[PDB]
Image (cartoon, coloured by chain):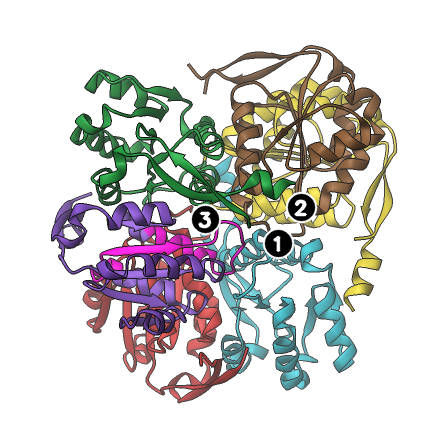
Chain colours: A red, B purple, C green, D brown, E yellow, F cyan
Amino acid sequence: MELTTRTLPARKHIALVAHDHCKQMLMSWVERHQPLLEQHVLYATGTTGNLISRATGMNVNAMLSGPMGGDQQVGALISEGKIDVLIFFWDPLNAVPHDPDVKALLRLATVWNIPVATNVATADFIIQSPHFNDAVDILIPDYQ
Amino acid sequence: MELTTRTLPARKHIALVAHDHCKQMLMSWVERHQPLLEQHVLYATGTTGNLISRATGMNVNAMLSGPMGGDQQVGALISEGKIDVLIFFWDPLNAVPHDPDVKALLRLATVWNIPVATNVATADFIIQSPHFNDAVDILIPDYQRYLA
Amino acid sequence: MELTTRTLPARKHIALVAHDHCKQMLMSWVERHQPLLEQHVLYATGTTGNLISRATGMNVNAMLSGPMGGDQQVGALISEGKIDVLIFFWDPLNAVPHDPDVKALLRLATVWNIPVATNVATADFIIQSPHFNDAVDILIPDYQRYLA
Amino acid sequence: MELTTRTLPARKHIALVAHDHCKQMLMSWVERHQPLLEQHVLYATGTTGNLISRATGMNVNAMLSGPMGGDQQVGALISEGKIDVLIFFWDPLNAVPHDPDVKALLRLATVWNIPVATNVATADFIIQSPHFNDAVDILIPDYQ
Amino acid sequence: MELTTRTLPARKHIALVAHDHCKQMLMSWVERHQPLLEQHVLYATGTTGNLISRATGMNVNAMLSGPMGGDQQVGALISEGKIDVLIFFWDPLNAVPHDPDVKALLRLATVWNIPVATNVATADFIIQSPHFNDAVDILIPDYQRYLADRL
Amino acid sequence: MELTTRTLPARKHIALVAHDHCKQMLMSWVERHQPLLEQHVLYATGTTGNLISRATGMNVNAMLSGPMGGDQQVGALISEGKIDVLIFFWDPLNAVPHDPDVKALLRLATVWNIPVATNVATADFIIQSPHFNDAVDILIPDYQRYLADRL
């Protein structure tokens, strides 16, 4: 298809999504990078937003939990160019009822070409990247 | 889980979604019920919005095509109580790349208990139902209570 | 493909299918519409048949539970034109082992164009529809013509 | 769960199911074993039944094509103990619209413990087995 | 797709894989055919293999547990022609997190045309087959031709 | 789940995988970072690898084509700690027959905690990261402990 350009603002809109058994893994990650994260706009599904808020004092825009539609809310925001980075620690060792939503969200993040991390190693590599705090240009499908 | 109720307004917010091979099928349905549909609010993914306004003169809230995120936009609206009826003519005879999105949307419509039709027979039965133009209450998950 | 029509009889053959966590949901629906359901022919998978006859006194054609093949038995009947309405309250919040069977049954109900409800709101709209007790024709794939 | 017993008759009810690109592979297999197959009861989905009938002169009970419900018809027969052997040459190199039906049929054949072959090698091993023409006892779930 | 042939050796490389609710069912089958199985080359996923080895004293080359990658290790071996028979008792009555791995493994066993059994009835029919202990030729995709046409 | 650590070497073992409609997109990315990529150890599935090698003269250890088993071969290597980075440009706009293999590979890369990129933006962020050429410790499931508790 035809590609065009979109610029990720220097101050990114980051979505943090985790499955129950990966909540701690994500909490730990957020705490460890709080200083950098404190400079961006945060979104989270379910109670995770509350957990982060209470633990770090950082403001987090909350969305519905995954099973209730939160993944599709984030997917919608991504398709509209309102989310620039997705940190999605889904559980590869547990069968979840909303698996279609999980796969759909990952499909959309791939299509819209935004930085996506599904594990700590990838998340660390991305957040430590030089241009994480810079305005970055990415190729995206030209919807028109 | 905890349940509560919500009112579907007399004037319904209807999402019309169709796969390429089911486009004519959806249009024929809209055209067969134009008079009744004129009293409601329409939403449509992809090119369907324009086809409808061009063919019927009705205004439609357009959203992205399915493969590009339209299904999730509709699903997000359903979860927020902004869509009351879903007419989703998905293709049962063709493999689609965004199948996960299709299944996710249908999963959400089931969870949030809104009228959903995936074929013409179901759509006709729903639209001919007496309370389609009335305000009706439905039982839905009580997310707020559940959260706390 | 080639299409043709088939008549849904005034007296409908209704399949009632529910997942464990949706059993009470299905029963409540049957009990809320007992008077109307008494005029039709009921089929049910698993233990639902007995629960219905015990609670309402209505006779039900019992089939195997979903995991054991009940979904395919119903799907086979739909494809043969022996089931006219499908009330399938599947669980959108629990992963089931026979998910393929669930998706296959819903795929077939869509293909054969019969009224299908996956939640209470849709089921209520369908059963309250004027022609639920009337003979109605539906457009279906013309397999015979297609074959030749 | 509780298992019980069922006896596969010496004369088996065999279902032959193939995807478009595996039609020839199955035709060839049926021809090569016609003498043995001629002793059993055959079922097939779609036009394959007609193809076999016209090519071998053998009688084949036809079912609907896969996309139209044929796989579920066969699945139903299996769950009712009316099919004893399933020869299902599905296509592992092509995405099919009725994939759920394909997986459901294979799931049922596994649950009901009947001999199932999805490729020629397995089919040959099964048909050349000594007890293929004998009444055989198999463990099955005790539905009651 | 062009086909060529490959020869399964007399002593087969057998992969034994079972889901938790099917492990006892697999163990019983193994015990029942232990004398014959001892003649062949055995491989098994993490847990399954260790239980077999422990109970029968048989040599079983163990791979990682299915969820941790064992199914893909077995899949890779099948594609490389190093596994000749697959005994995979997967659970049809329980949803597993590594379902994609399960389907991928079965897809590959189908593609590479090796004898595959997913239940006891099929396993018994295969192991009782005359040529189970013989070298036997099977038709397999001709990869060389397949790649060339792709390039 | 118990976690331990593993160290990714300075010169990484990189798997490059692309679906047909994404191959040009992957090739362009490779060409753009060729000088750096030449320093690392490269692996690729059937077709992808050969096209890269042919166009850039770079050494690429080729595996089988994805549909023929290459994805599982890559999955097996990740689980054995032999692949450190996965660049997988799968096609989100086309249905593929080996979808289970695709999902299984991504599931394993997630489980084993290695850097994974499924689009250009993520790939660029990763390769431009400071520690891409450094030895870096990652947390991984402690398999030994995981197995023991299963037995």
Q: C140 or E66: nearer the eye?
A: C140
Please determine whether, in this image, residue D12 is positioned above or below residue F128. above
Q: Secondary structure at mark 1?
A: loop
Whether residue A55 is in magenta: the answer is no
Which chain does the residue under circle 3 lie in?
A: A
Q: Which residue is mark 1?
A: F97
Quarter of the image for residue E49 reads top right
Seen at 17% across and 26% down, the residue is C35
Q: Which mark is residue D91?
A: 2
Query: In screen coordinates, is C15 left or right of C54?
Result: right
Q: Assess whether residue B86 is covered by the magenta stretch.
A: yes
Give the left or right position of residue D79, taking residue B34 as reference. Answer: right
What residue is shown at x 48% (from left), y 69% (from top)?
A: A110
Amino acid type of disc 3?
Leu
Disc 2, disc 3: CB below 8 Å?
no
Amino acid type at mark 1? Pro
Kindly report the distance in space between the C-alpha atoms of the residues bearing marks 1 and 2.
9 Å
Q: Which secondary structure, mark 2?
A: loop
Real-space Cα separation, disc 2 to disc 3, in angstroms = 28 Å
Tell me which segment is drawn in magenta. B78-107
* Residue A120 x/y as whole percent: 44, 65
Rendered residue at 60%/38% (across/down):
D65
Q: Which mark is residue A93?
A: 3
* Element marked by disc 3: loop
Chain for disc number 2: D
**Residue F43 location, x and y as percent?**
69, 67
Q: Residue at x 67, y 59 (%)?
A: F66
| Residue A28 in sight here | no
- Residue D11: in sight, yes or no? yes
